[PDB]
Length: 59
Length: 50
Ligand SMILES: [Ca+2]
Ligand SMILES: [Ca+2]
Ligand SMILES: [Ca+2]
Ligand SMILES: [Ca+2]
Image (cartoon, rainbow over all chains, first blue to last red):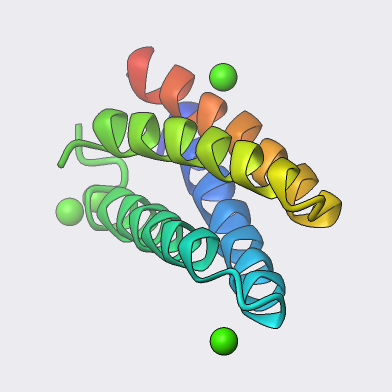
């Protein structure tokens, strides 16, 4: 894949793990709203990661 | 959703958590949220270029 693609992959992975850290810290505080947003973020970062991999070097 | 649009979603949502975390003095969460936003910016820039 191209440099752009490798950056999207690397960034997507970092966000996924960071969102997971917020999910833990938010629920530790019983901050349900913040947790739900972090969940949505994790879902989007995961989707970017899987979609980018699925199309790796294709274009 | 395109990768570009999913990065846009994260960019904004990350700053919304930043704002709500600040309101709760959840500083560790706020810092992570801001870092998430910066990384989303890179996906957005890369997806824009591509
Ligand atoms: Ca709880
Ligand atoms: Ca493919
Ligand atoms: Ca391929
Ligand atoms: Ca930004």
